[PDB]
Amino acid sequence: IANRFTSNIKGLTQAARNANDGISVAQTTEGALSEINNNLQRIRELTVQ
Amino acid sequence: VGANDGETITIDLKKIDSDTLGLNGFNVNGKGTITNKAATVSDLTSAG
Amino acid sequence: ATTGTNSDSDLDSIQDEIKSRLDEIDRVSGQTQFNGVNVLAKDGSMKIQVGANDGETITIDLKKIDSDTLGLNGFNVNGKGTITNKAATVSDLTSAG
Amino acid sequence: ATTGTNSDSDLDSIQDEIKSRLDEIDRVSGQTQFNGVNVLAKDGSMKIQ
Amino acid sequence: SAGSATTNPLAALDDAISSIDKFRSSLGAIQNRLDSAVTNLNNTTTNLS
Amino acid sequence: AKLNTTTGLYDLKTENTLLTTDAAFDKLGNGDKVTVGGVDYTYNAKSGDFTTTKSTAGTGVDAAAQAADSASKRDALAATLHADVGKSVNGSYTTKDGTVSFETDSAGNITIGGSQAYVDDAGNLTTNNAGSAAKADMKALLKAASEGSDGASLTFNGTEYTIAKGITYQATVSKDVVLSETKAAAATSSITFNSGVLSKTIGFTAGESSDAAKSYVDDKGGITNVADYTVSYSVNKDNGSVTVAGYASATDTNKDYAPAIGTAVNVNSAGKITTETT
Amino acid sequence: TVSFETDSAGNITIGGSQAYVDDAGNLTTNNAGSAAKADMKALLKAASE
Amino acid sequence: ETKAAAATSSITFNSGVLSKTIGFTAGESSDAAKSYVDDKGGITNVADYTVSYSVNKDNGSVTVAGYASATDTNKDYAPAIGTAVNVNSAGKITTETT
């Protein structure tokens, strides 16, 4: 049972690290999307003009 | 996300560019390109 | 979301977030595990020996916690709700036979 | 390694480490010896009077 | 001509939260009673020794 | 077990139940063929039901026979079954080299693109009429297809019908239904067990097999050729132990159920007779 | 009433498929009795006769 | 002795319930029976099956359209028509995409 618990603890810690990496991926993609959105807003203003 | 097999979370991504938003020949002033199409055997038969 | 000022796209985004969190509830319920036993995925009970003779036991009751046992299945908050139906006419009156 | 964020080089490095440790398992199994008897290399039995 | 949107979302969520709270309370009571059992076992072991 | 007076041994006889329709249906597999009442059914395990091929009609050998009348009445019956008054259904009517959509609402009314179509002499489907040859009905369409020089193919929500140059079509019947006709009376139903390589046909009348075939199930389930199960036990007068001293069977049995001779006989936990020690 | 798409050099097409004219004069998309004559000249002749 | 000589042997396969008897000439089967095994193993007694593929000239996509069998075959090896065919890892022509 101690072996099983050690395996589970190590796996869960590594999974937490993986989830942190995924959060980083999401943040980077969202920043790129925000810049694209600002460009689109400016283009719409130019079209209205 | 888990310690056993199959315990995953999926992040879907999208191909975002001019092509997937349209806007290709935005052409506000009326001067631009279309990059029309590539022909096929059905088009040739229709043309005769 | 229940506010009537929200538009269709806003309701769609809110329901997307709701569906994501319901999926998280289901995932945590399915994947929570202790010593190879899914504590939250079964409606059984566990017996603990606390005395030195037979019969000295304490029972822990577990409940199957997920979407199904809490309802929330089609938690369709982005739906349409009560909608007034259109009046009948002669064309579909005859179509009915 | 099973996380999908890792790239090909990352997976290659991880599998290199995995191969090294599997080689260690095999080496320990082969070379563990007591009084000229390979305890872990045979599926037999020992009799004690 | 009733539609497909959930009728009473707040009531359904309240029922779910109430069920979760009841099960948590049951677990807490079981844990307290188990700790009391532990203390009694230690005292009895000391006296028997 | 009964004591044999002439030999002094103890003989134990075990009976074997004849093959039944329920057991046969349980052992039915994919591609199995069942013949009851002269009509062949093919079992499907994917949907778990019997598929059949039914022709329209035709029994007489000449024009002045009941074949034409049976064909006409079966065509009428199929058209009536195609009523579907409550809701509309879509299909397709295909000639030898051409096809056309089909959308009927009720009473077999032909509607193409919201406009009622008509059937010609040769089964042709046309939105127009030449010489007032409308006859826009399912019965008329089926009759024109049957009398046409060239056959046709009809695709509907259910099975696909083929009108030959008679209509051949697939149909579905329930396994419980087929069981009911098989066990209803003294039928001549026969079941063919096919493994894709090995095949055997068993003909049984209202349950038990009457084709002089030793089909039985009591041993461990399944099918066996052992008619009777008889084994001889010798009791030692001094020790008191019971040993197996051979066996005899009505059929050959190919020594398949042969127990070891001279092995001590043990009583199972449930109380049966078994040679296993533990 | 039938709506048909005439093609170059003379042809009859209904719903993207070649159409045939009945001998009596009706228009169809499927041939019956081995009498197709899928041509607008044939359609006109059949209508006249 | 069966393979070398031009004898007439008989082989019976029994599963305990189902039985099949096959005649054999000097290395082959001459009992007017199909008795073919080459597909994947087991006696499938099918002479040959021909699969017809339709090629769409607009894009080059190839689909399955048409099955022919010299025997009944119960449509054992007949794929459903209209299914796009692909190429396996070994270069074979196969329908599944796994």
Image (cartoon, coloured by chain):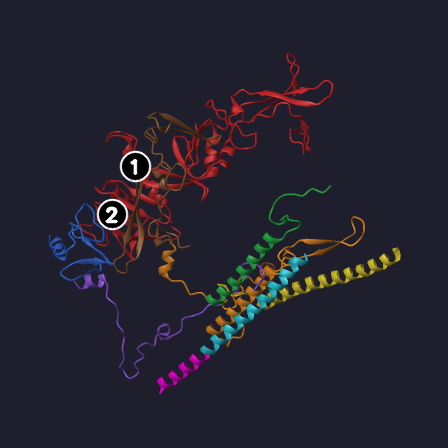
Chain colours: A cyan, B purple, C orange, D green, E yellow, F red, G blue, H brown
Q: Callout 1: helix, strand or loop? A: helix
Instruction: Where is residue C88? Give x, y as percent.
Output: 40, 62
Q: As displayed, is residue F44 above or below residue E13?
A: above
The reply, left or right, for residue F157 in relation to residue G12 is right
Q: Residue at x 38, y 58 (%)?
A: C93
**Do the residues at pointers 2 and 1 share their chain?**
yes
**Counting residues from the N terminus, which is met first, the one under dot 2 or under dot 1?**
1
Q: Quadrant of the N terminus of chain B?
A: bottom right
Q: Which residue is mark 2?
A: F95
- Please report contact status of discs 2 and 1: CB closer than 8 Å, yes or no: no
Q: Is residue A45 magenta?
A: yes
Q: Which residue is mark 1?
A: F71
Instruction: Where is residue F11? Give x, y as percent.
Output: 63, 19
Instruction: For mark 2, name the chain.
Output: F
Instruction: For mark 1, name the chain.
Output: F
Q: Quadrant of residue B31?
A: bottom left
Check disc 2 and give the amino acid type. Answer: Thr
Residue B10 in view, yes or no:
no
Q: Residue at x 21, y 55 (%)?
A: G18
Q: Callout 2: helix, strand or loop? A: loop
Nearer the camera: disc 2 or disc 1: 2
Q: As displayed, is residue D11 above or below residue F231?
A: below
Circle 1 residues within 10 Å: few <14, some 14–19, many ≥20 = many
Check disc 1 and give the amino acid type. Answer: Ala
Magenta-drawn stretch, dominant element (helix, strand or loop): helix
User: Which one is nearer the viewer's eye here, F197 or F97?
Assistant: F197
User: Which one is nearer the viewer's eye here, E25 or C45?
Assistant: C45
Residue A26 in view, yes or no:
yes
Q: As displayed, is residue C66 above or below residue H43?
A: below
The magenta region covers: A33-49
The span from disc 2 to disc 1 (Cα, nearest Å) is 21 Å
